Amino acid sequence: GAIRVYASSTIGNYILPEIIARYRRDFPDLPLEMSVGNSLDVVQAVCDFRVDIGLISGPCHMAEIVAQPWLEDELVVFASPASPLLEGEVTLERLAAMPWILREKGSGTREIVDYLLLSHLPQFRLSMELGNSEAIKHAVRHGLGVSCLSRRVIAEQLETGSLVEVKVPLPPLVRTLYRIHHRQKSSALARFLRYCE
Amino acid sequence: GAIRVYASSTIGNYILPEIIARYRRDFPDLPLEMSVGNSLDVVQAVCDFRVDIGLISGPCHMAEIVAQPWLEDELVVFASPASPLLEGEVTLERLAAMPWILREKGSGTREIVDYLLLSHLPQFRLSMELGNSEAIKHAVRHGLGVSCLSRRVIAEQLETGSLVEVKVPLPPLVRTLYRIHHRQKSSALARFLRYCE
Protein backbone atom coordinates (compact mmCIF):
# COMPACT_ATOMS: atom_id res chain seq x y z
CA GLY A 1 0.00 0.00 0.00
CA ALA A 2 3.00 2.27 -0.41
CA ILE A 3 2.67 5.51 -2.36
CA ARG A 4 5.13 5.60 -5.27
CA VAL A 5 6.36 8.97 -6.55
CA TYR A 6 8.74 9.43 -9.50
CA ALA A 7 10.32 12.89 -9.73
CA SER A 8 13.41 14.61 -11.07
CA SER A 9 16.51 15.13 -8.94
CA THR A 10 15.79 18.84 -8.44
CA ILE A 11 12.23 18.07 -7.33
CA GLY A 12 13.29 15.04 -5.30
CA ASN A 13 16.11 16.77 -3.42
CA TYR A 14 14.86 20.36 -3.04
CA ILE A 15 11.04 20.38 -3.33
CA LEU A 16 9.68 17.01 -2.15
CA PRO A 17 11.60 16.76 1.19
CA GLU A 18 9.53 19.50 2.84
CA ILE A 19 6.34 18.00 1.40
CA ILE A 20 7.34 14.49 2.48
CA ALA A 21 8.01 15.69 6.04
CA ARG A 22 4.57 17.25 6.47
CA TYR A 23 2.86 14.25 4.84
CA ARG A 24 4.70 11.72 7.02
CA ARG A 25 4.00 13.56 10.29
CA ASP A 26 0.26 13.59 9.52
CA PHE A 27 0.24 10.00 8.19
CA PRO A 28 3.04 7.99 9.83
CA ASP A 29 1.73 4.54 8.85
CA LEU A 30 1.53 5.00 5.07
CA PRO A 31 4.77 3.83 3.41
CA LEU A 32 6.35 6.05 0.77
CA GLU A 33 8.54 5.20 -2.22
CA MET A 34 10.33 8.01 -4.05
CA SER A 35 12.34 7.36 -7.21
CA VAL A 36 14.52 9.89 -9.04
CA GLY A 37 14.51 10.08 -12.83
CA ASN A 38 14.01 12.34 -15.81
CA SER A 39 10.77 13.05 -17.67
CA LEU A 40 10.83 10.16 -20.15
CA ASP A 41 11.60 7.53 -17.49
CA VAL A 42 8.84 8.91 -15.25
CA VAL A 43 6.23 8.91 -18.02
CA GLN A 44 7.09 5.29 -18.85
CA ALA A 45 6.66 4.25 -15.21
CA VAL A 46 3.27 5.99 -15.01
CA CYS A 47 2.14 4.29 -18.22
CA ASP A 48 3.40 0.94 -16.91
CA PHE A 49 1.60 1.53 -13.57
CA ARG A 50 4.95 1.16 -11.79
CA VAL A 51 4.47 4.47 -9.92
CA ASP A 52 1.42 6.50 -8.89
CA ILE A 53 2.47 10.16 -9.21
CA GLY A 54 4.99 11.67 -11.61
CA LEU A 55 6.70 15.07 -11.30
CA ILE A 56 8.50 16.02 -14.51
CA SER A 57 10.10 18.99 -16.25
CA GLY A 58 7.93 20.00 -19.20
CA PRO A 59 4.43 19.12 -20.37
CA CYS A 60 2.85 15.83 -21.48
CA HIS A 61 0.33 15.53 -24.31
CA MET A 62 -0.62 11.85 -24.04
CA ALA A 63 -4.35 11.18 -23.77
CA GLU A 64 -3.85 8.54 -21.05
CA ILE A 65 -1.92 11.02 -18.86
CA VAL A 66 -3.50 13.71 -16.68
CA ALA A 67 -0.87 16.47 -16.77
CA GLN A 68 -1.24 19.78 -14.92
CA PRO A 69 1.25 22.63 -14.42
CA TRP A 70 2.63 22.44 -10.89
CA LEU A 71 5.50 24.84 -10.10
CA GLU A 72 7.68 27.39 -11.84
CA ASP A 73 11.44 26.88 -11.60
CA GLU A 74 14.12 29.46 -12.41
CA LEU A 75 17.54 28.26 -13.53
CA VAL A 76 20.63 30.36 -12.81
CA VAL A 77 24.16 30.56 -14.18
CA PHE A 78 26.59 30.39 -11.26
CA ALA A 79 30.33 30.24 -10.64
CA SER A 80 32.90 30.08 -7.87
CA PRO A 81 33.46 33.35 -5.96
CA ALA A 82 37.05 33.37 -7.30
CA SER A 83 36.00 32.91 -10.93
CA PRO A 84 37.36 35.44 -13.46
CA LEU A 85 33.85 35.52 -14.96
CA LEU A 86 32.74 37.59 -11.95
CA GLU A 87 35.20 40.36 -12.90
CA GLY A 88 34.16 42.65 -15.75
CA GLU A 89 30.93 43.08 -17.66
CA VAL A 90 29.42 39.73 -18.63
CA THR A 91 29.13 39.18 -22.39
CA LEU A 92 28.01 36.24 -24.51
CA GLU A 93 31.62 35.72 -25.63
CA ARG A 94 32.91 35.75 -22.05
CA LEU A 95 30.28 33.17 -21.08
CA ALA A 96 31.30 30.89 -23.96
CA ALA A 97 34.98 31.35 -23.05
CA MET A 98 34.63 29.66 -19.66
CA PRO A 99 34.74 25.86 -19.36
CA TRP A 100 31.18 24.63 -18.95
CA ILE A 101 29.78 21.89 -16.72
CA LEU A 102 26.25 20.64 -17.40
CA ARG A 103 23.83 18.02 -16.15
CA GLU A 104 23.30 14.72 -17.94
CA LYS A 105 21.58 14.57 -21.31
CA GLY A 106 17.85 13.92 -21.09
CA SER A 107 17.40 15.95 -17.90
CA GLY A 108 15.13 18.98 -17.76
CA THR A 109 18.03 21.12 -16.56
CA ARG A 110 20.24 20.20 -19.52
CA GLU A 111 17.31 20.73 -21.89
CA ILE A 112 16.83 24.28 -20.60
CA VAL A 113 20.51 25.23 -20.84
CA ASP A 114 20.77 23.74 -24.34
CA TYR A 115 17.93 25.65 -26.02
CA LEU A 116 17.56 28.77 -23.84
CA LEU A 117 21.19 29.50 -22.90
CA LEU A 118 23.82 27.72 -25.02
CA SER A 119 21.89 28.41 -28.24
CA HIS A 120 22.51 32.16 -27.83
CA LEU A 121 26.22 31.73 -27.00
CA PRO A 122 29.18 31.15 -29.32
CA GLN A 123 29.77 27.47 -29.93
CA PHE A 124 32.17 25.66 -27.60
CA ARG A 125 33.26 22.15 -26.68
CA LEU A 126 31.58 21.07 -23.45
CA SER A 127 34.21 20.48 -20.78
CA MET A 128 32.31 18.21 -18.37
CA GLU A 129 28.91 16.53 -18.17
CA LEU A 130 28.10 15.41 -14.62
CA GLY A 131 24.91 13.48 -13.93
CA ASN A 132 24.43 14.83 -10.41
CA SER A 133 24.01 18.29 -8.92
CA GLU A 134 26.35 17.58 -6.00
CA ALA A 135 29.27 16.69 -8.27
CA ILE A 136 28.60 19.86 -10.29
CA LYS A 137 28.67 22.12 -7.23
CA HIS A 138 31.98 20.59 -6.12
CA ALA A 139 33.48 20.99 -9.60
CA VAL A 140 32.35 24.63 -9.84
CA ARG A 141 33.59 25.37 -6.31
CA HIS A 142 37.04 24.12 -7.38
CA GLY A 143 37.20 26.50 -10.35
CA LEU A 144 36.87 23.74 -12.96
CA GLY A 145 34.19 25.75 -14.76
CA VAL A 146 30.76 27.33 -14.61
CA SER A 147 27.33 25.70 -14.70
CA CYS A 148 23.59 26.37 -14.81
CA LEU A 149 21.27 24.84 -12.21
CA SER A 150 17.94 25.59 -10.59
CA ARG A 151 18.12 28.30 -7.94
CA ARG A 152 16.59 25.83 -5.47
CA VAL A 153 19.62 23.55 -5.86
CA ILE A 154 22.24 26.22 -5.11
CA ALA A 155 20.12 28.37 -2.76
CA GLU A 156 22.14 27.33 0.30
CA GLN A 157 25.44 28.04 -1.46
CA LEU A 158 24.20 31.37 -2.84
CA GLU A 159 23.36 32.48 0.71
CA THR A 160 26.69 31.48 2.28
CA GLY A 161 28.61 32.84 -0.71
CA SER A 162 30.35 29.60 -1.70
CA LEU A 163 28.67 30.06 -5.10
CA VAL A 164 27.86 33.32 -6.89
CA GLU A 165 24.99 33.96 -9.28
CA VAL A 166 26.10 35.32 -12.67
CA LYS A 167 23.92 37.92 -14.37
CA VAL A 168 23.45 36.94 -18.03
CA PRO A 169 22.27 39.46 -20.69
CA LEU A 170 19.55 37.04 -21.79
CA PRO A 171 15.93 36.42 -20.80
CA PRO A 172 15.68 34.50 -17.51
CA LEU A 173 15.82 30.71 -17.66
CA VAL A 174 12.40 29.78 -16.27
CA ARG A 175 10.79 26.36 -16.73
CA THR A 176 7.49 24.80 -15.66
CA LEU A 177 7.33 21.61 -13.61
CA TYR A 178 4.34 19.35 -14.24
CA ARG A 179 2.54 16.78 -12.10
CA ILE A 180 1.23 13.72 -13.95
CA HIS A 181 -0.76 10.58 -13.19
CA HIS A 182 -2.56 7.93 -15.20
CA ARG A 183 -6.12 8.69 -16.30
CA GLN A 184 -7.22 5.16 -15.31
CA LYS A 185 -6.08 5.82 -11.73
CA SER A 186 -7.60 7.36 -6.30
CA SER A 187 -7.75 8.25 -2.61
CA ALA A 188 -4.59 8.72 -0.52
CA LEU A 189 -3.08 9.70 -3.88
CA ALA A 190 -5.24 12.82 -3.60
CA ARG A 191 -3.98 13.34 -0.04
CA PHE A 192 -0.34 13.39 -1.12
CA LEU A 193 -1.29 15.65 -4.04
CA ARG A 194 -2.89 18.06 -1.57
CA TYR A 195 0.44 18.31 0.27
CA CYS A 196 2.21 19.13 -3.01
CA GLU A 197 0.38 22.48 -3.25
CA GLY B 1 37.06 12.14 -27.66
CA ALA B 2 35.37 12.57 -24.29
CA ILE B 3 36.08 10.11 -21.49
CA ARG B 4 32.87 8.46 -20.28
CA VAL B 5 32.67 7.21 -16.69
CA TYR B 6 29.64 5.43 -15.18
CA ALA B 7 29.67 5.24 -11.38
CA SER B 8 27.28 4.97 -8.45
CA SER B 9 25.93 8.04 -6.67
CA THR B 10 28.21 7.54 -3.66
CA ILE B 11 31.26 7.25 -5.93
CA GLY B 12 30.08 10.03 -8.22
CA ASN B 13 29.33 12.55 -5.46
CA TYR B 14 31.95 11.74 -2.79
CA ILE B 15 34.90 9.95 -4.44
CA LEU B 16 35.15 11.06 -8.09
CA PRO B 17 34.97 14.88 -7.53
CA GLU B 18 38.46 15.04 -6.00
CA ILE B 19 39.80 12.74 -8.73
CA ILE B 20 38.06 14.74 -11.47
CA ALA B 21 39.56 17.98 -10.15
CA ARG B 22 43.15 16.71 -10.27
CA TYR B 23 42.60 15.10 -13.69
CA ARG B 24 41.06 18.25 -15.19
CA ARG B 25 43.80 20.57 -13.91
CA ASP B 26 46.48 18.38 -15.50
CA PHE B 27 44.47 17.81 -18.71
CA PRO B 28 42.14 20.77 -19.32
CA ASP B 29 41.37 19.98 -22.98
CA LEU B 30 40.06 16.41 -22.59
CA PRO B 31 36.25 16.44 -22.19
CA LEU B 32 34.72 14.30 -19.45
CA GLU B 33 31.31 12.65 -19.21
CA MET B 34 30.19 11.22 -15.86
CA SER B 35 26.92 9.30 -15.50
CA VAL B 36 25.39 8.08 -12.24
CA GLY B 37 23.81 4.64 -12.00
CA ASN B 38 23.81 1.35 -10.14
CA SER B 39 25.88 -1.73 -10.89
CA LEU B 40 23.59 -3.42 -13.42
CA ASP B 41 23.08 -0.27 -15.49
CA VAL B 42 26.84 0.40 -15.50
CA VAL B 43 27.72 -3.14 -16.60
CA GLN B 44 25.21 -2.90 -19.46
CA ALA B 45 26.74 0.39 -20.64
CA VAL B 46 30.25 -1.10 -20.58
CA CYS B 47 29.07 -4.14 -22.54
CA ASP B 48 27.28 -1.85 -25.02
CA PHE B 49 30.43 0.32 -25.33
CA ARG B 50 28.38 3.33 -24.23
CA VAL B 51 30.91 4.23 -21.51
CA ASP B 52 34.62 3.56 -21.03
CA ILE B 53 35.11 3.04 -17.28
CA GLY B 54 32.64 1.63 -14.77
CA LEU B 55 32.76 1.99 -10.98
CA ILE B 56 30.29 -0.34 -9.28
CA SER B 57 29.43 -1.79 -5.87
CA GLY B 58 30.28 -5.49 -5.87
CA PRO B 59 32.23 -7.79 -8.18
CA CYS B 60 31.69 -8.84 -11.80
CA HIS B 61 32.36 -12.34 -13.13
CA MET B 62 31.77 -11.82 -16.86
CA ALA B 63 34.62 -12.96 -19.10
CA GLU B 64 34.34 -9.84 -21.29
CA ILE B 65 34.75 -7.54 -18.26
CA VAL B 66 38.06 -6.70 -16.57
CA ALA B 67 37.01 -6.21 -12.94
CA GLN B 68 39.45 -5.29 -10.16
CA PRO B 69 38.81 -4.35 -6.52
CA TRP B 70 39.17 -0.59 -6.14
CA LEU B 71 38.17 0.85 -2.75
CA GLU B 72 36.68 -0.30 0.53
CA ASP B 73 33.56 1.52 1.72
CA GLU B 74 32.09 1.41 5.22
CA LEU B 75 28.36 1.99 5.67
CA VAL B 76 27.04 3.50 8.90
CA VAL B 77 23.67 3.66 10.65
CA PHE B 78 22.93 7.28 11.51
CA ALA B 79 20.14 9.37 13.01
CA SER B 80 19.22 12.92 13.94
CA PRO B 81 20.92 14.27 17.09
CA ALA B 82 17.46 14.51 18.71
CA SER B 83 16.52 10.91 17.90
CA PRO B 84 15.34 8.73 20.81
CA LEU B 85 17.53 5.96 19.37
CA LEU B 86 20.58 7.84 20.69
CA GLU B 87 19.29 7.49 24.28
CA GLY B 88 19.80 4.11 25.93
CA GLU B 89 21.73 1.02 24.93
CA VAL B 90 21.17 0.13 21.28
CA THR B 91 19.54 -3.26 20.72
CA LEU B 92 18.33 -5.09 17.63
CA GLU B 93 14.73 -4.56 18.76
CA ARG B 94 15.27 -0.83 19.29
CA LEU B 95 16.78 -0.55 15.81
CA ALA B 96 13.78 -2.32 14.26
CA ALA B 97 11.39 -0.11 16.27
CA MET B 98 12.49 3.09 14.53
CA PRO B 99 11.01 4.09 11.16
CA TRP B 100 13.56 3.24 8.49
CA ILE B 101 14.57 5.17 5.37
CA LEU B 102 16.60 3.37 2.72
CA ARG B 103 18.05 3.98 -0.72
CA GLU B 104 16.36 2.75 -3.89
CA LYS B 105 16.20 -0.94 -4.72
CA GLY B 106 19.04 -2.12 -6.94
CA SER B 107 21.62 0.19 -5.37
CA GLY B 108 24.72 -1.13 -3.65
CA THR B 109 23.78 0.73 -0.48
CA ARG B 110 20.33 -0.87 -0.28
CA GLU B 111 21.86 -4.27 -1.05
CA ILE B 112 24.23 -3.94 1.91
CA VAL B 113 21.55 -2.85 4.38
CA ASP B 114 19.21 -5.62 3.22
CA TYR B 115 21.52 -8.61 3.72
CA LEU B 116 24.03 -7.36 6.32
CA LEU B 117 21.81 -5.18 8.56
CA LEU B 118 18.05 -5.72 8.15
CA SER B 119 18.47 -9.50 7.98
CA HIS B 120 19.66 -9.56 11.61
CA LEU B 121 16.87 -7.25 12.84
CA PRO B 122 13.24 -8.04 13.66
CA GLN B 123 11.01 -7.69 10.62
CA PHE B 124 9.38 -4.32 10.01
CA ARG B 125 7.50 -2.43 7.31
CA LEU B 126 9.84 -0.01 5.54
CA SER B 127 8.65 3.55 6.12
CA MET B 128 10.33 5.36 3.21
CA GLU B 129 12.47 4.47 0.20
CA LEU B 130 14.23 7.54 -1.23
CA GLY B 131 16.33 7.22 -4.37
CA ASN B 132 18.80 9.95 -3.43
CA SER B 133 21.18 10.50 -0.53
CA GLU B 134 20.29 14.20 -0.19
CA ALA B 135 16.59 13.48 0.33
CA ILE B 136 17.52 10.84 2.91
CA LYS B 137 19.71 13.22 4.93
CA HIS B 138 16.92 15.81 4.98
CA ALA B 139 14.35 13.21 6.06
CA VAL B 140 16.61 11.90 8.84
CA ARG B 141 17.46 15.43 9.98
CA HIS B 142 13.71 16.08 10.39
CA GLY B 143 13.24 13.05 12.66
CA LEU B 144 11.26 11.07 10.08
CA GLY B 145 13.43 8.01 10.74
CA VAL B 146 16.89 6.49 10.65
CA SER B 147 18.95 5.33 7.69
CA CYS B 148 22.17 3.60 6.65
CA LEU B 149 24.57 5.28 4.21
CA SER B 150 28.26 5.27 3.39
CA ARG B 151 30.36 7.24 5.86
CA ARG B 152 31.69 9.29 2.93
CA VAL B 153 28.17 10.56 2.21
CA ILE B 154 27.46 11.81 5.75
CA ALA B 155 31.05 12.68 6.71
CA GLU B 156 30.36 16.43 6.61
CA GLN B 157 27.21 16.05 8.72
CA LEU B 158 28.94 13.71 11.19
CA GLU B 159 31.62 16.37 11.76
CA THR B 160 29.24 19.30 12.30
CA GLY B 161 26.92 17.14 14.42
CA SER B 162 23.79 17.52 12.28
CA LEU B 163 23.83 13.71 12.02
CA VAL B 164 25.01 11.20 14.63
CA GLU B 165 26.52 7.78 13.98
CA VAL B 166 24.69 4.95 15.76
CA LYS B 167 26.74 2.07 17.16
CA VAL B 168 25.11 -1.22 16.14
CA PRO B 169 25.91 -4.54 17.94
CA LEU B 170 26.65 -6.19 14.59
CA PRO B 171 29.74 -6.64 12.42
CA PRO B 172 30.62 -3.45 10.53
CA LEU B 173 28.91 -2.85 7.19
CA VAL B 174 31.90 -2.81 4.83
CA ARG B 175 31.62 -3.26 1.06
CA THR B 176 34.12 -3.34 -1.81
CA LEU B 177 33.86 -0.99 -4.78
CA TYR B 178 35.09 -2.36 -8.11
CA ARG B 179 36.45 -0.70 -11.25
CA ILE B 180 35.46 -2.34 -14.54
CA HIS B 181 36.12 -1.90 -18.25
CA HIS B 182 35.63 -3.96 -21.38
CA ARG B 183 38.31 -6.50 -22.25
CA GLN B 184 38.22 -5.44 -25.91
CA LYS B 185 39.14 -1.87 -24.88
CA SER B 186 43.36 2.12 -24.27
CA SER B 187 45.46 5.21 -23.60
CA ALA B 188 44.02 8.27 -21.82
CA LEU B 189 41.73 5.69 -20.22
CA ALA B 190 44.83 4.52 -18.37
CA ARG B 191 45.60 8.13 -17.42
CA PHE B 192 42.21 8.61 -15.75
CA LEU B 193 42.60 5.20 -14.10
CA ARG B 194 45.94 6.36 -12.67
CA TYR B 195 44.17 9.30 -11.02
CA CYS B 196 41.63 6.92 -9.44
CA GLU B 197 44.34 5.37 -7.24
Image (cartoon, coloured by chain):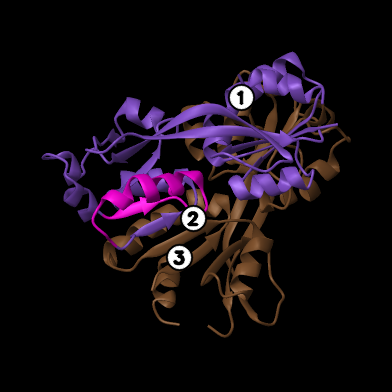
Chain colours: A brown, B purple
Q: Quadrant of residue B79?
A: top left
The residue carrying mark 2 is B105
> Residue B156: x and y, percent?
40, 28
> Residue A26: x and y, percent?
28, 66
Residue A80 has which mark? Answer: 1
Question: Magenta residues?
Answer: B99-124
The three-letter amino acid code for the residue at tag 2 is Lys
The residue carrying mark 3 is A196
- Is residue A78 shown in magenta? no
Among numbered discs 3 and 1, the one appearing first in the sequence: 1
Task: Residue at the far top: name it.
Answer: B26
How packed mark 2 is, by other alpha carbons closer than 10 Å (few <14, some 14-19, many 20 or more), is some
User: Under tag 1, what secondary structure?
Assistant: loop
- Do the residues marked 2 and 1 share a common chain? no
Q: Is residue A88 visible?
A: no
The three-letter amino acid code for the residue at tag 1 is Ser
Give the Cα separation between the discs numbered 2 and 1.
35 Å
Q: Is residue B31 visible?
A: yes
Task: Residue at the far left: name it.
Answer: B88
